Length: 141
Length: 144
Length: 141
Length: 144
Image 1: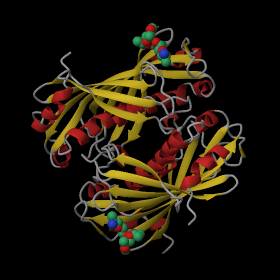
Image 2: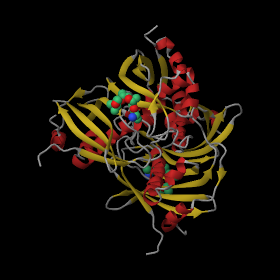
Image 3: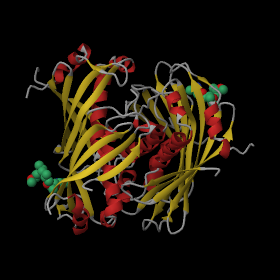
Image 4: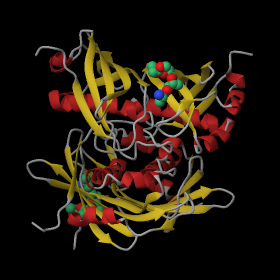
């Protein structure tokens, strides 16, 4: 279990006039996937994130290979690519679950942990709890 | 006067774009890329809509953004777009995000790769970038 | 079972600087709830909705009684208020599921079924399949 | 010259706002109410932000919209807002949506009820509408 899975049934609001899913939604799903991971494996991070901790997204990207239709069942699999003192690089595989599974997109995010008054924040070491939650996903043993 | 120009999209940050942290949720930066590129189309090649309603599709092959600072509600944003690369059937767009103030602060940089296609939704074949679009992007084409 | 239930865990993107859920999201959940109802009870409507059928929202409204926080578990219960020849009035109860359940909002939508070229559409009788799917929700027997 | 005026928010419809049907997804109309009301604040009472960051909260008690026509991508929209009612602690805003063309077509009408509050997030007490805000809305106050 080296990845976290977020499942989603595509809705009409996510489509555009061409009939497929508008590209922005793929980036939105990265955030949804990453926060559900926190909800299920490190809920304590919200209290921090509701306090003074901040998760700053340094980079967000997605490459698209195929299209998605309304009501396609999607599985976004998140993996930990790299964990540094203060940052985390996350990888996302987007699978359309059907008669057969199809990789419709692949993305990445780099996030930095930070604390301090808005405008006067500084990078902080990845919270111990989050590092523990990442245990099964870390390449390092 | 023939120096490559950028197409500028200006936006005043609202509250819907902010999260509990107090700054702009990252997704909005990618949204603004689409908004910027479509307002460019609206102003320079509105006739592309008729094509987009028929069989023409602008398929985004890649979208990315790197973030350097924070944006707060009511901040004045300027998204500057340039055509950085044009092949037979694809276009690469560059986006520079600036917070307008005394000193314009670069808050992020983005990029998109788009492929032109025509065909039965699901049975699409690549097509050469529409002539009208190529001409429209001409003045905003970056050489470097 | 006179209502359909859509469950959702509130995420960070749905909050604003004040820490609660931005009001627009409540209206978005009505659409999400109504389409998941279709997905589970009248999936054939998509094929129609991907063809020439159109669900035109004539009215959408929501009244707010309390606030919602990130990661609160929400239950949106949808009921059929009225079913006419061509229209449907839907009611939505928004419950925050916690130690105790709290009614945080209540909304309504009126939708009209229509067919025809965009700009030249006309109201059509509610599709037989949808009427059947509404059987357990109809006041009429 | 003293006739009640409306505050106008103009928006060019984009592709993100459209659904597979080809018109604007209904949710966007409610979005535009917030956008319109906040741009009003930005232009007429920007200092409210400092209050919104501290303890002031604009709680939306009710939001509604009725739809009469369709809006397509690239349509020019005008959302006109008026203060329709002002009590000690609440405000009711009216929104008229028009598609701008030769003949401006009314495509929808909306309304919002907002309550002013201050206090520990969850332990909020109602407060009288801020003086600065009341004055800012003055010229856009509707009597009927």
